[PDB]
Amino acid sequence: MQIFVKTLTGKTITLEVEPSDTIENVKAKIQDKEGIPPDQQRLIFAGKQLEDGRTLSDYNIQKESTLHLVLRLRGG
Amino acid sequence: MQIFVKTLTGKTITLEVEPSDTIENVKAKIQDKEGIPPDQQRLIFAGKQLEDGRTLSDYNIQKESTLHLVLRL
């Protein structure tokens, strides 16, 4: 399924993912596209921050859902 | 230096480490105490998951810091 990620500049990228993918997996995908290591990423959906160990489906993230990427400020 | 690890039960153990130890090395030490292979561990410090690749020092982990062990599901 396709989901969208709003990047640090407001631009939106498209990713192919699976409902069973973990948030950690998604962060790796974002690293590949954006060059931000997972430990520096905060991912936000529906106004809340997602935790690593959950699956996308655990958060009810569906086709064409949008996540927001935020850079951690206090380091890794 | 001594750090602490909260284990899957909530019980806290001590590990002997050095600031230059990598997270992968730390997972190895935890495997020796807890019997959970490194590729099934998630380690959390200060509310965030630590990456293989980095040293304890890279995360400003110090003496008496507490790491949290979580089982990958």
Image (tube, coloured by chain):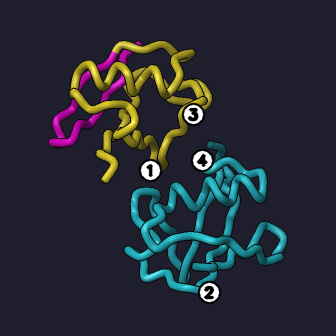
Chain colours: A cyan, B yellow
Mark toward the viewer: 4 or 1: 4
Horizontal relation, residue A52 to residue B40: left or right? right
The residue identified by callout 3 is B59
Question: Taking B22 as reference, is A20 left or right?
Answer: left
| Mark 4, residue position | A39
Q: Which residues are magenta?
A: B1-15
The answer to whether marks 3 and 1 mark residues whose Cβ atoms lie closer than 8 Å is no
Query: Looking at the image, is A67 positioned above or below residue B9?
Result: below
Residue at (78%, 58%) from the top-left corner? Answer: A34
Residue on which disc 2 sits: A64
**Residue A70 as seen in the image, left or right of residue A43:** right
Mark 3–mark 1 distance (CA, rounded to whole Å): 12 Å
- Say what secondary structure mark 1 lies in: loop
The residue at the point 21 percent across, 32 percent down is B12
State how far apart marks 3 and 2 are (Cα).
Answer: 35 Å
| Front residue of A75 and A60 | A60
Alpha carbon distance from label 2 to label 4: 25 Å
The residue closer to the viewer here, B9 or B71, is: B71
Q: Earlier in the sequence, mark 2 or mark 4?
A: 4
Residue designated by label 1: B47
The picture places residue A66, in percent across and down from the top left corner, at 63, 82
| Mark 4 → mark 3, Cα distance in angstroms | 10 Å
Check if mark 2's residue and mark 4's residue have beta carbons within 8 Å: no
Query: Is there a contact, CB below 8 Å, between mark 4 and mark 1?
Result: no
- Give the residue type at disc 3: Tyr
Q: Which mark is in front, 2 or 4? A: 2
Q: Sort mark 3 into few (<14), some (14-19) or many (20+) by Cα contacts within 10 Å.
A: some
Which sits in the foreground, A74 or A34?
A: A34
Q: Is disc 2 on the same chain as disc 3?
A: no
Q: Amino acid at mark 1?
A: Gly
Residue B49 among magenta residues? no
